[PDB]
Image (spheres, coloured by chain):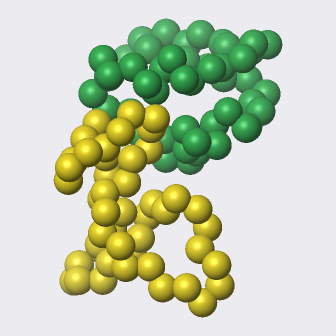
C-alpha cells in the first residue's frame, strides 16, 4: 500500500540484459512488445517496486 | 464458446490474402525454443472468450 515510485528519465532503458535474464518468472507487456521496445522513445519511465 | 481460434504471434506481417495455419510454438526472445516448449515460448493460437 506504500509502493515506492522512482522516476527514470534521461537515459537508455536497455532491455537486452533484462529480458534475456532467466532469473525472472513472469513478465508481460500489455501495451508494448520487447521486440519494438528498443525502437520506441519514452518521455519518462517510473518504476513502482 | 472457445472453439474460435486466432493467431497472436508471427515472424513477420503476412501478405494480403494469405492463410497461415502453422501451429509451431512462438519464441519471443533470442533464446532457442526447442521441442514443443521452452523459456517464454507461447502458443500462437489463443481462443475467444
Rendering quarter of residue A36: top right
Q: Quadrant of residue A15?
A: top right
The residue sitting at 58% across, 62% down in the picture is: B12
**Eyeballing the image, is B48 above or below B41?**
below
Q: Is residue B30 left or right of residue A34?
A: left
Quarter holding residue B32: top left
User: Where the N terminus of chain B falls, by quadrant?
Assistant: bottom left
Residue shown at the point (43%, 25%) measured from the top left: A20
Residue A14 location, x and y as percent?
A: 62, 20
Q: Colour of chain B?
A: yellow
Q: Is residue B5 left or right of residue A32?
A: left
Instruction: Indicate left or right for A8 with A19 as reference.
Output: right
Q: Position of residue A3 (x, y in %)?
A: 44, 14
Toward the viewer: A2 or A32? A32
Instruction: Choose between B8 and A30: the one closer to the eye.
Output: B8
Could you tell me which residue is drawn at 59 percent across and 74 percent down? B14
In the picture shown, does residue B30 fall above or below B18?
A: above
Q: Position of residue B15 (x, y in %)?
A: 64, 78
Where does the image place residue A21, in percent across and percent down from the top left? 39, 20
- Quarter of the picture holding the C terminus of chain B: bottom left
State the green chain. A
Q: Is residue A15 visible?
A: yes
Residue B46 in view in this figure: no
In this view, B49 is above or below B36: below
* Residue at (73, 37) in percent of width and height: A40
Amino acid at each position: 500500500y506504500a509502493w515506492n515510485r522512482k522516476r527514470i528519465s534521461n537515459c537508455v532503458a536497455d532491455y537486452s540484459v533484462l529480458y534475456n535474464s532467466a532469473s525472472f518468472s513472469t513478465f508481460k507487456c500489455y501495451g508494448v512488445s520487447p521486440t519494438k521496445l528498443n525502437d520506441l522513445c519514452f518521455t519518462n519511465v517510473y518504476a513502482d517496486s | 464458446n472457445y472453439n474460435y481460434l486466432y493467431r497472436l504471434f508471427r515472424k513477420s506481417n503476412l501478405k494480403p490474402f494469405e492463410r497461415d495455419i502453422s501451429t509451431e510454438i512462438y519464441q519471443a526472445g533470442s533464446t532457442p525454443c526447442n521441442g514443443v516448449e521452452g523459456f517464454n515460448c507461447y502458443f500462437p493460437l489463443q481462443s475467444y472468450g
